Amino acid sequence: AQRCGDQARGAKCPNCLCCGKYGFCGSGDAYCGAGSCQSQCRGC
Image 1 (cartoon, helix red, strand yellow):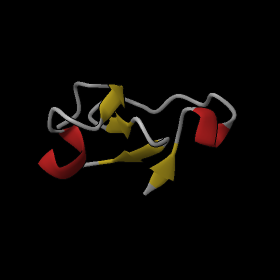
Image 2 (spheres, rainbow, N blue to C red):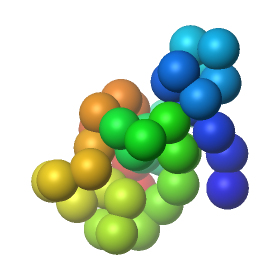
Image 3 (cartoon, rainbow, N blue to C red):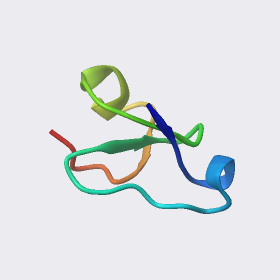
Image 4 (cartoon, rainbow, N blue to C red):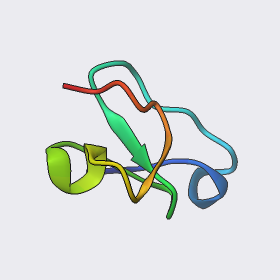
């Protein structure tokens, strides 16, 4: 579990991961699915 976006001073996340609009970078369709994705919308 890693924080991104405004929740991380505008920090970006690596590939194979999804950055939740709520500055929350995680995995799984739970955060990768369409509805809470903002950045890095191409994770595994």
